[PDB]
Image (cartoon, rainbow, N blue to C red):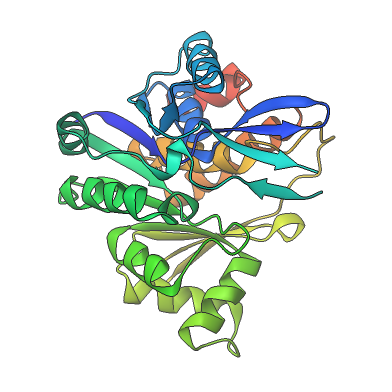
Amino acid sequence: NNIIVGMGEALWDVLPEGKKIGGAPANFAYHVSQFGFDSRVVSAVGNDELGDEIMEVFKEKQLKNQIERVDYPTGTVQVTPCYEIKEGVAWDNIPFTDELKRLALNTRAVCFGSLAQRNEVSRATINRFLDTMPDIDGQLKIFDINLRQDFYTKEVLRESFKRCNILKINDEELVTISRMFGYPGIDLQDKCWILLAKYNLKMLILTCGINGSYVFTPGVVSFQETPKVPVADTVGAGDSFTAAFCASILNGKSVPEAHKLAVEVSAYVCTQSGAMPELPVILKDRLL
């Protein structure tokens, strides 16, 4: 089966200058659909104006979804270089429905993060989705760990490492994990090797910002420099990386080919103001 799912938060980044849609899930779903995949955003919003607004934007972007309405406000991040991630919100309460069960059974690749597991309701839904979803036929379960503030526990991380088969992590988050799990003093690569082997990962993607990015597979490292481009805004670039990497791997590309496309896609997205720019056709051609 066939469907690619981005699952987690969907919210408004409410800046003094106005508000903007945010959420790694929708961004991943969007970018994977640029590469011809049938994608769904799985989240929840409130029966409120902000929720209606989100749903209209996704309609406008032609972004297909299985978003439920729940009895909690649509999520927001109040922005002040500082972020208040409002709690007790709709995306903390994504329900595990009969329909979501069926979606999980039919899902080819999913990407999920840590933030949307902070609350017991969404955490339970996410884990049940993953445990329902098959993986014996090359399906991808991508944990784009994305640590936010202090919204993570050791148990949430450990269970997610167990459920995923691809981890995407940055070099500072890798330091944090290594501290939590008792190997802080070793080499960067050795930290990655532990995670790759311990959790039987197909791949581990390590991003190091201006210092490039790595993809680890057993016995093999792929490394790419980060291009310097004229940044408009980096919003959505990391999600577009994950989406392009996913698309490439599912298309049958090698890891080095996937890694290269992911870097180029991220670089392009950084040149654009919004999180969901239409991708260049010459980058889409890479999956021919």
Estimate the x, y position of residue 5 in percent, counting from the top left: 35, 34
Please name the residue shown 77% across and 24% down the image. Answer: 18
Task: Quadrant for the N terminus, please.
Answer: top left
Q: Which residue is drawn at 17% across and 37% down?
A: 101
Q: Quarter holding the C terminus?
A: top left
Numbered marks: total:
0
Q: Which of 88 and 216 is in front in this view?
A: 88
In the image, residue 36 sits, relative to residue 231, either above or below, namely above
Q: Which residue is drawn at 43% across and 21% down?
A: 47
Q: Is residue 101 above or below residue 20?
A: below
Q: Where is residue 216 in the image (x, y as percent from the top left)?
A: 47, 64
- The image quarter containing residue 164 is bottom left
From where the camera sits, is residue 274 visible? no
Q: In this view, does 11 lie to the left or right of 199?
A: right
Q: Nearer the viewer, residue 89 or 226?
A: 89
Question: Dividing the picture into quarters, in which one does residue 220 lie?
Answer: bottom left
- For residue 195, above or below residue 108: below
Determine which quarter of the picture holds residue 96. top left
Residue at 60%, 24% in the rendered image: 276
The residue lying furthest to the top in this view is 60
174 sits to left or right of 82? left
